[PDB]
Image 1 (cartoon, protein in one colour):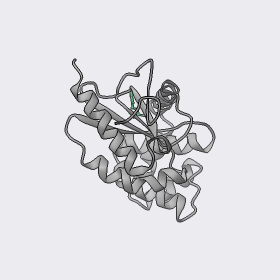
Image 2 (image 1 turned 90 degrees about the vertical axis):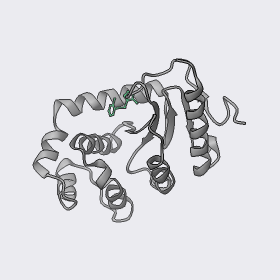
Image 3 (image 1 turned 45 degrees about the vertical axis):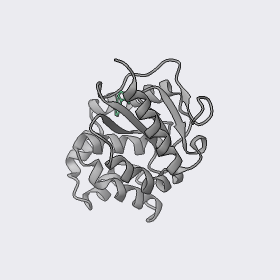
Image 4 (image 1 turned 135 degrees about the horizontal axis):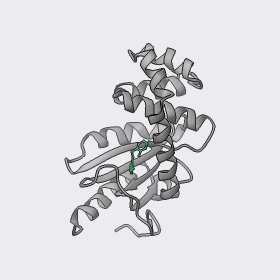
Length: 187
Ligand SMILES: Cc1ccccc1CSc1nncn1N
């Protein structure tokens, strides 16, 4: 019952997906974004209930300044295989504890409190691989033509956000609908 152009738009140039063969769902976010923080209790449980042919990805929006710093922290944690376990703690630190997490040294100190290897965090943060991932994330956001967060993209093809869908639960119902649209498509 959704209308292309209203609750979601279709990208005229679809973007490749991270895991070919699965229906991708991307949430573009920034740890410091209050709406992103407020969306977490809705999107997190939904993301954990997704079927086997769907691949949920968080992608930091690297829109400059502190967004890039926090995004680089995110990618470092993903690379280390620890982001899932400290995800909520980072949001809480920033929004409830008023921690800035604005330099790698501050990040490492905080994250060590959550069990994250400090030396490995710092080495990874400054690594060439993370530089490459930052550039890829920037190029992806440009391709999605995203200008704010949180924003969802399904299968590199459909872009929508909380405002366009009409609320947080509505956003995920819309995601479900678009996932079904893609599952039904011929390949
Ligand atoms: C490509 C990258 C860079 C940085 C972090 C995570 C990723 C994987 S996400 C992705 N890759 N191709 C489409 N798409 N959504």
